[PDB]
Each structure stands twice: as C-alpha cells, then as structure tokens.
Amino acid sequence: SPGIWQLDCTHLEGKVILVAVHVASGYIEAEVIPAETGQETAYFLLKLAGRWPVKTVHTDNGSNFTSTTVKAACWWAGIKQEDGIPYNPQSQGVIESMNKELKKIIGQVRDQAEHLKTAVQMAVFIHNHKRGYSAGERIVDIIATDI
Amino acid sequence: SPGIWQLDCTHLEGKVILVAVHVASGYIEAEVIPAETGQETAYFLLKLAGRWPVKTVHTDNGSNFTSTTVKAACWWAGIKQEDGIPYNPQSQGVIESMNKELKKIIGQVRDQAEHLKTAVQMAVFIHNHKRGYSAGERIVDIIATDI
Ligand SMILES: COc1ccc(CNC(=O)c2cc3ccccc3cc2CN(C)Cc2cccc(OC)c2C(=O)O)cc1
Ligand SMILES: COc1ccc(CNC(=O)c2cc3ccccc3cc2CN(C)Cc2cccc(OC)c2C(=O)O)cc1
Image (cartoon, rainbow over all chains, first blue to last red):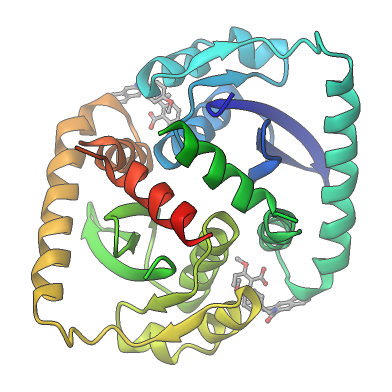
C-alpha cells in the first residue's frame, strides 16, 4: 500500500483534469490536458513515477488500461498497471467526493488566475496541505516507514 | 534544510530545462519550457510547493529574483524567496556537475522518445532512483524526520 496509486479523470471548463491519488494518504498530483489520450496519460504516469515510488497504478478506465502507450510507460517506469474496478464499493464514493471537493477548491481560487491549470495547481496545494496530519505529511510518513 | 530548494536553468535543443533541486538530498523535479519567463518560473514553483513542503527557494538568477510574478507565487505558496549567490563556493560546481550529469542521462534516453520533455522526465526518474540510498529515499527520510 505505500506504492499504490489511483488514476482519476474529471472535467471542467471543457478541459480534462487528470488526477493521481495516493490511496493510503489522500495525497494528489494533477494536471490539465485538452483531452484524455493514451499519450497524455502515459506522460503523466512517467512524471509521477519519477517523483514518488509508484509500484501499482489502478487505471481510471478501460481505454487507459488497454492503451499500449500507457502499458509502455508503465513498463518503462516499473509500474504494475492494474484495472480500477471498485472491488471495495467505498472506492466510487471516495473518488466522487474527491472530485467534488477539488472542484469546490478550484471555484474558491478560480478568480486568482487567468488559466485553469494555475487554479488546479492552487487546489492541489490546498488539498495536500489541509489538516491532525495533512495528506502531504501522511504520504511522506508512510513511505519513510516503508523504506 | 528539509525545506530548502535551489532553482537551476539549463539549455538543450534550443529549449530551456527548468530544474528544482532539494539541496539536502539531491532530489530533483524538472520541466521543459520554450524560454525562462517569470510566469513559467512562478507556475513551476507553485507546482513544486503543492507537492513538497517548500520553505525556501534560492532563485537561479536576478531576473527571477526580481520578477513580481515569481514573488507573487512565492507569497501565494508560503515560500521564502532568496537569492542564489554561491556563498559556499562548492555550489557552482555542484550545479554545474548536476547539469552535465542530467544532459548525459538525457543523451542516453533521447532515442526512446520523440519529444524532449519525455526524455527529460526519463532523466528525472533515473536521477532520483539512482543508488546506499537514492535521492528519492533521502528526501522522504529527511522530511519524515522533520515532521
Ligand atoms: C503561479 O504564479 C502566480 C502568480 C500570481 C498570481 C496572481 N494572479 C494574477 O496576477 C492574475 C489574476 C487574474 C485573475 C483573473 C483573470 C486573470 C488574471 C491574471 C493574473 C496574472 N497571471 C499572469 C497569473 C499567472 C502567473 C503565472 C502563471 C499563470 O498561468 C500559467 C498565471 C495565470 O494567470 O494563470 C497567480 C499565480
Ligand atoms: C511516456 O510514455 C512513453 C511510452 C512509450 C515510449 C516509447 N517510445 C516510443 O514509442 C517512441 C519512440 C520514439 C523514438 C524516436 C522518435 C520518435 C519516437 C516516438 C515514440 C512514440 N511516442 C508516442 C512516445 C511518447 C509517449 C507518450 C508521450 C510522449 O511525449 C509526450 C512520447 C514521445 O514520443 O515523446 C516512451 C514514452
């Protein structure tokens, strides 16, 4: 579980927000892309795995699970690519609630920047710092304990 | 020192590679941009500070130190913006050696992707994983100990 991440795709302003959640901590990384493609998802995972010790990724949908480009990136980066079927039924709700919360924060910062990507990174900041520990503190502690 | 980062700008293929180094560990994050502007640097720092507990940034040059946009991002993200004058003379050499090493790795992966940004993220991955601890292990341990 220190190495388990979940992909999540949500939409705002006609754009796509791609999110990776570290399941055990709730820590997130996110980016804005014009549309979800295999190449964009692959590049996002490459970035993620260079920054955190990503062992397993639960993909957000069947297209990214199938994508040969995503599979290639996971091979390159030493990631076990898995499906994202909510075997635990709590998972749907948790991701739903995360997207709602993220969109709420984005709304609270949206008039502080021209570009959606800026607002999204502000929201990532606020989410990861929110406390009692923050998600950023939890991920570091979990991984440090594992090392 | 757990919160101290150094900015670094290097050039390849007519593009700019912007690098943030966590000084105590050698862990890096990096991105490719067409040129180093205040807005790009500001956005890069916002991303960084949402992902790690960035307390202090030593800026890479006087233009980024002066930039009101960079100062605004540092204000927003709770970062102390400082100059990057190598008071310790070993600092020049260490950054010089880091850029040379990064360019070497980029060369070793360059034919595995069309786009420079992909090669740069491959290089970030290799750098942070290289072992005896890796930079990625060191940064997590340093920060966890601090928390
Ligand atoms: C991350 O560094 C900062 C630094 C300062 C601020 C404070 N906010 C403003 O100064 C502002 C507020 C606006 C509010 C409504 C409409 C337009 C706006 C345009 C602006 C000016 N721009 C240049 C900010 C900006 C900078 C760098 C990259 C950016 O995007 C890549 C953007 C952006 O605008 O997204 C936000 C973020
Ligand atoms: C990170 O995910 C992967 C997945 C697979 C590979 C294996 N490499 C190739 O398949 C390849 C090698 C090339 C070698 C010389 C010239 C062109 C090339 C074009 C390609 C095909 N592209 C689509 C890879 C690619 C994918 C996603 C985003 C990308 O950039 C944003 C690029 C890119 O090309 O930069 C690398 C990285």
